[PDB]
Image (cartoon, rainbow, N blue to C red):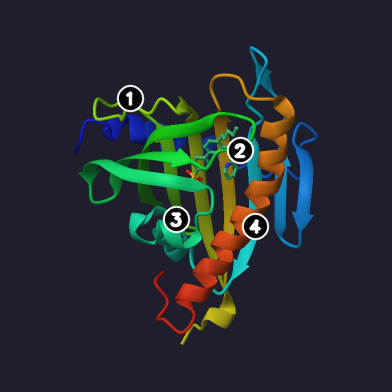
């Protein structure tokens, strides 16, 4: 029980309600890039001339569990092993053993000014409602206000609502028989102004690169370890 428990519950529930839905049949999502099981979609949205384009991706990763994927996504201690777009990050506050508030700066993308972010990051297990449903592991990263926020005059403050939502299929269980189904959503307000073409090019390049890189990292770090369901 920290002061964000209720907000966390709301953000997680919204993602469970809305973000998990399959968008194969939904023409409102534009499928931008497909590489195998990796499917990356966006909606073209601008507010006050700033690109907000919602990002939604699915993926199916052999050999790892949702629990493992989420631990690796969440655990700050391995962040620098997979992240390629971060210049700096600091843990601002520990709320609980499954929740922290993080400040980070993104590498500058010329010619836009650098962005920073301040967000609560929480990892949660959502039990299968019925014996028919999969359990879900989720990480949610969403912007919050904080006082120990750094002054950084080089940066415009972006605001994010990201979730990595994982269900695991199992087919001695070996990694050969496990598949992790990922839905990843990112809604990013870059703040300020940045050229629309730049924001779209960054999204189109960096999201598939992240998903490929990050998932491969989890496969590589877990191979030959006992499975953490
Ligand atoms: C001019 C450039 C503006 C950059 C806008 C931007 C700010 C923040 C973020 C962001 C993206 C993912 C997360 S997370 O998944 O929670 C993991 C922790 O880092 C947190 C923040 C994205 C983006 C915009 C594009 C973009 C896309 C994939 C990689 C990098 N940048």
Give the left or right position of residue 111, taking residue 93 as reference.
right
Q: Is residue 27 above or below residue 209?
A: above
Q: Could you tell me which residue is drawn at 56 percent across and 33 percent down?
A: 187
- First in residue order: circle 4 vs circle 1: 4
Quadrant showing the N terminus: top left
Q: Which residue is mark 1?
A: 145
Q: Nearer the viewer, mark 4 or mark 3?
A: 3
- First in residue order: circle 4 vs circle 3: 4
- First in residue order: circle 2 vs circle 1: 2
Is the CB atom of the residue marked by disc 2 within 8 angstroms of ligand 1's nearest atom? Answer: yes
Residue 59 badge: 4
Give the left or right position of residue 201, taking residue 65 as reference.
right
Foreground residue among 2 and 143: 143
Would you say the residues marked 1 and 3 are in contact, meaning their CB atoms lie under 8 Å apart?
no
Cα separation, mark 4 vs mark 2, equals: 27 Å
Q: Residues within 10 Å of mark 3 (few under 14, many from 20)?
A: many
Q: Could you tell me which residue is drawn at 49 percent across and 67 percent down?
A: 65
Q: Where residue 158 sits in the image (x, y, percent)?
A: 49, 28
Q: Which residue is mark 3?
A: 73
Cα separation, mark 4 vs mark 3, equals: 15 Å
Q: Mark 4 falls on what kind of element?
A: strand
Q: Which residue is mark 2?
A: 109
Ligand 1 shown in quarter: top right
Q: Nearer the viewer, mark 4 or mark 1?
A: 1
Q: Nearer the viewer, mark 2 or mark 1?
A: 2
Cα separation, mark 4 vs mark 1, equals: 32 Å
Q: Where residue 189 sits in the image (x, y, percent)?
A: 55, 26
Give the left or right position of residue 35, taking residue 114 as reference.
right
Give the left or right position of residue 7, taking residue 32 as reference.
left
Q: Residue furthest left?
A: 1
């Amino acid at each position: 029980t920290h002061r964000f428990v209720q907000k966390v519950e709301e953000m997680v529930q919204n993602h469970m309600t809305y973000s998990l839905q399959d968008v194969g049949g939904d023409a409102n999502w534009q499928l931008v890039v497909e590489e195998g099981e990796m499917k990356v979609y966006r909606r073209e949205v601008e507010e006050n001339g700033i690109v907000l384009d919602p990002l939604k991706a699915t993926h199916a990763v052999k050999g790892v569990t949702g629990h493992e994927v989420c631990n690796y996504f969440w655990n700050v201690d391995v962040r620098n092993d997979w992240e390629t777009t971060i210049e700096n990050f600091h843990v601002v506050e520990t709320l609980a053993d499954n929740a922290i508030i993080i400040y980070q700066t993104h590498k500058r993308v010329w010619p836009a000014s650098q962005r920073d972010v301040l967000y609560l990051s929480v990892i949660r297990k959502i039990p299968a409602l019925t014996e028919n449903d999969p359990e879900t592991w989720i990480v949610c990263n969403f912007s919050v206000d904080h006082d120990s926020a750094p002054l950084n005059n080089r940066c415009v403050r972006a605001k994010i609502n990201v979730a990595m939502i994982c269900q695991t299929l199992v087919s001695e269980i070996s990694r050969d028989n496990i598949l992790c189904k990922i839905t990843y959503v990112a809604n990013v307000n870059p703040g300020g102004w940045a050229p629309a073409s730049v924001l779209r090019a960054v999204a189109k390049r960096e999201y598939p690169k992240f998903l490929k890189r990050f998932t491969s990292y989890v496969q590589e770090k877990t191979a030959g370890k006992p499975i953490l369901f």
